[PDB]
Structure formats: C-alpha cells, structure tokens
Amino acid sequence: SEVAHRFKDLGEENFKALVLIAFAQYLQQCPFEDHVKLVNEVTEFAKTCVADESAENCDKSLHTLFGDKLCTVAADCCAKQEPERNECFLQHKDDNPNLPRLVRPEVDVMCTAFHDNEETFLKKYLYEIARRHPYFYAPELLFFAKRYKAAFTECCQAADKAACLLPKLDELRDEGKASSAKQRLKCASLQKFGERAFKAWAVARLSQRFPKAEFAEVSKLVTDLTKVHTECCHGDLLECADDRADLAKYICENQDSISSKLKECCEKPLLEKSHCIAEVENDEMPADLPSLAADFVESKDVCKNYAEAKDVFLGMFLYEYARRHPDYSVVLLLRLAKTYETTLEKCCAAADPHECYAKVFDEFKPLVEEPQNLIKQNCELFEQLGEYKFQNALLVRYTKKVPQVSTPTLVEVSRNLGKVGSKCCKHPEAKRMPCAEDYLSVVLNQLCVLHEKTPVSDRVTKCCTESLVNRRPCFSALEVDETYVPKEFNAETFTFHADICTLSEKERQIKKQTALVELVKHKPKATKEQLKAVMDDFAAFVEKCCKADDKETCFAEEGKKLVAASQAA
Ligand SMILES: CN(C)c1cccc2c(S(=O)(=O)N(C)CC(=O)O)cccc12
C-alpha cells in the first residue's frame, strides 16, 4: 500500500496538507469546499489502509486514486487512463489562471477567523496559493504556512495588530512569489531540457556552496536533489516531501564532510531545517587548490579521459571550476563548461590534440567579461535613474525587441526585470554576477512560459528554446523588430478615467506603464526623447482630473486634450 507508506512517514497533518495542495494545483478553478471534501474522503481511506494494508484498493498507485477522486468533480482527461490521464492534467496547469485578485480584509476580521477556526484559516491559505502557483515547491509551501501561522498567532494578541501583521504579511507575499519563481525555472529546466541540464546546474550550484565537499559527495547530493524536484515538478508531492526529508537528514548527519555552516541548520525543526539548508551561504574556499590548467589543458591524457567517460569528466571539470569561483554566476560556469566541451570535441579529432585545445582559456576571457560589463553598465544606470524610471526604460527597450508580446506580459516582465537592479546592484563587484544573472534567468523564464501559452513572436520562441543557459545573451542581442507593422490607435486603450484615482500609487504607475507600451507598439521608431516628453504629460492628466470637482467626465474632456496632444508628438 503506497498511501499507507507515505502516511506513516509524513503523519496526518502534513499528509492532509500535501494532498490539498496537489488538488488545488491540478484543478485550479474548483472551489475550496470540494477540495476539502475530497481531501477528507481520501485521508479517511488512507487510515483504513494503515490497518488493513489490503482493504479496498490500498494496492493501487497514488496517481490512480488521486485521479479518480478529482474525476468525480471535473473531462477528456478523465477519459484517459493511468499514465495519459496524469500527464493530461500536468499539461493543463495554468501559469496565469484567470483568478480574482486576492484582497485581504481588515486585521480585525482575519484575527477573528483565525482564532475561531484555525485549521480552516490555514487550509484556505494553502488553497489560494497552490491554485495561483501550480508549481510552488510543495514542501516549502508547508514551511511558509507555519510562518503565516506564527504571524497571526503573535500579532493578533498585541497592541496594534495592523502594525504587526500587515508588514510580516508583505514580506511573506513577496518571498512567496520569489520562491514560486525559482521553482518554476527548475521545473521548466527539467521539463523542456531534460535531467541532464538540471544536473549540470545542480553540480555547479552545489560545488560553489560546498567547496570542501568531494566530487563523489556532491554527485550523491545532486542525484537525490534531482529526484526530489523531478518528483515535485511532476506532481508526486507526497514522495517529494518524503525524499526531501531524507536528504535533509543525511546532509545533517554528514555535516563535516559537506560544509561547516550547516551547524545552525541541523539544530531546528524539520520544515525549518530543510529551508535552512537549501539557502545556506557558501562555505569558505579550501586553501591550497592546484591550478585547473594542470589536469584540464596541460595534461596530455585529456582526450583519453574525455573519451573514457565524457560525463564524469566534464562534470568534474564543472565542479573543479565552480568550487573556486563563487564570484561567477551559475549560467556563466555552464557556458564555460559548454565551450570546453565543444573544444575537446573538435580538438580530440585533430592530429595533435594538445596543440588545438591548448589555448582554451583564451576562449573563456570574452565570456567572463560580457556579463561583468553588462552588470557594471546597467547598475550605473540604475543608480542614476532610480527604480521606477529604470523600469520604464526596460519597458521601452523590450517592446521594441518583441512588439507582438501582450501588453500585460510586457509590463509584468519589465517591472520584475527592474527589481533586479535594487536587489543586486547594492552588492560589491564580487557578488553582483550570481545575484544579477541568476535572477535574470528566472525573470526571463517567466516571459518564456507566459508566452508559450499563446505564441505570437518567433523571436521570443527562438530565444526561449534554442538554449537554456544562453537565454539572456539571446535576448540582449535583439535590438528592434525590423519587420513589425505598427498598430493603429484605439480610443478605449488611451482613455484615462477617474477610477485611476482610487487606485493605489503603484496601480497608477502600472497604468502609466501599460500606456507607455501601447504607445511604443504604435510608434516603434519613436525616440526616448519624445516618449519622456509625453509620459510626464500623462502625469498631469491624473493630478488634474482626479482633483477637480465632480468630474467623471474630465476623463473624457481632459482625456481629449490628452490624445490630441498625444497624436501630435
Ligand atoms: C543587474 N542589473 C542592473 C542588470 C544587469 C544586466 C542586464 C540587465 C537586464 S537585461 O534584460 O539583460 N538588459 C537591459 C540588457 C538588454 O536588454 O540587452 C535587465 C535588468 C537588469 C539588468
């Protein structure tokens, strides 16, 4: 009995939570009630299996049971069987479900609902998140949950809750989005590029983190870790949760052989331990490490070793190079690893290999500088424009690159691209690259997945499937779409009403930003000079209308003077 197995392992509290998440993530439209209903029914069934490990259908696989249970509330998918049925669902998850924005009632109402029924108050939380982020790292979602409970449990019994909860709640919403994003990259990697790619990323990323660990140790870690995520990303939430626990345990027992900063982590509860380990800082770099050139360019056995086990060899190369370069971004390490491979491949076929692959490191110099120069520039610019304006600059720049993309997606992607500035730039040269380019991999992955739902630009398609690690270079390379045909104005699109006044300060810029896009799609060839001169104008249109007697018509009048002058520039 599989259900029973996992149950004993996770216990009832986690088993129930993990199953509610799986249901919310599969059928994101169905109400809270129905999932709560199916979860209970299923959990009860599990209880009868722990006892009689041969009762009803305790023999069957998790998918079958889970599949049949949802199929009692859904159709084509449920028409299929075992494998096809499950893949079906996986292919229907929606990365941008059309759900109602989620608004939070007054502090008073939340504390009452929380104190009254606690289990419910949290289950609903899990439900609203798992349905909006169908790829949220399941185990980690339970961690946030405990943190969300501690927030209320503490703030609801204080002097000023609004002051105590609201903040902690914001910190959580953001980090929850961050978390969702990274995990979406891992799944995208695994699903669109294979496990080979995911492994490569794991090696470099972990070798940087555990410089002292041995190659055969990291290799072990990477193998398990791969499994964990392979499972979560495919929907096998229970086992993912289990395996992840195992991996946390192991890493803790064997600290000494892995890292010296894992102390703090292993002295805490499960959910907090796991989260702690995955985010630990890089251990100090071992003192006397030889030069790479020795065993990788100078040696005369290279090609031989490469031919014997190309995988273990390149893997070792990556580990070696990463471990001594925590200043390099994971994607940069992989680019290098890829250049070395292409070199051996052609060089090992020549007359005198040694001579051909002798100057490989000169190939590396250009690749290492490209990122450094780009980071240096854009942060210089960030420092001078500030976040909002910088976001607007990235807005104009990306709309000229891929004009077909939907205004909503452009606005979202460009806004996030701007945040990178604020997160990284403040770091010293030494840690800028990992921060900057790894974040950029996440944000552009967002653009890719949203776009794959409804492909309108071949340029985005090419850049998203050609290479995972070169996505950024691909995009930076693009300048302006020379074949794009300018759109034709629409009154409705540029009609500013008074309803923009009730909207928060942010919801405003967001409006002015959506207008900036619409304009660019209209005058691709326009210039940054003109655009600015026009933007500032829109600012005026809001201050006036919004504060000028009973005017819901100002929007049409002041708006007329707007489009008039707009059509002019
Ligand atoms: C760290 N941060 C300031 C950044 C460094 C390098 C490139 C960045 C980019 S970007 O998309 O690569 N970009 C502006 C380069 C380009 O469009 O060719 C966006 C946002 C922040 C960036």
Image (cartoon, grey):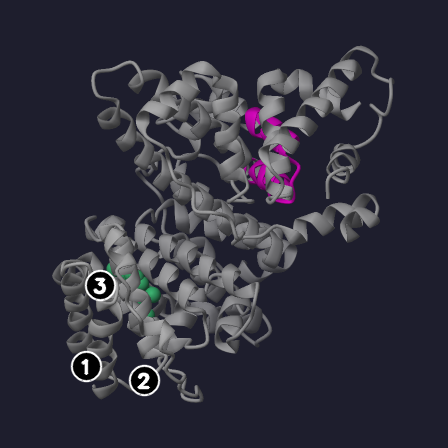
Residue 350, quarter of the rendered image: bottom right
From the image, state whether disc 3 or disc 2 is nearer to you.
Answer: 2
Residue at the image point whose x is 12% and y is 62% from the top: 384
182 or 19, nearer to the observer: 19
Q: Earlier in the sequence, mark 2 or mark 1?
A: 2
Q: Which residue is mark 2?
A: 523
In what quadrant of the picture does the C terminus appear? bottom left
Q: Secondary structure at mark 3?
A: helix
In what quadrant of the picture does the N terminus appear? top right
Confirm if mark 3 falls within 8 A of ligand 1: yes
95 or 54, nearer to the observer: 95
Q: Which residue is mark 3?
A: 390
Rendered position, 162 above or below 206: above
Q: Secondary structure at mark 2?
A: loop
Q: Earlier in the sequence, mark 3 or mark 2?
A: 3
Residue at the image point whose x is 38% and y is 77% from the top: 401
Main SS of the magenta segment? helix
Would residue 214 be found to the left or right of residue 77 on screen?
left
Q: Which residue is mark 1?
A: 530
Q: Amino acid at mark 2?
A: Lys
**Cα–Cα span, label 3 and label 1:** 17 Å
565 or 506, nearer to the observer: 565
**Cα–Cα span, label 2 and label 1:** 10 Å
Q: Amino acid at mark 1?
A: Gln
Would residue 230 be found to the left or right of residue 333 on screen?
right
159 or 379, nearer to the observer: 159
Rendered position, 104 above or below 475: above
Range of the magenta residues? Answer: 221-246
Q: Is residue 150 visible?
A: yes
Q: Are marks 2 and 1 in contact (CB under 8 Å)?
A: yes
From the image, state whether disc 3 or disc 1 is nearer to you.
Answer: 1
Quadrant field for ligand 1: bottom left
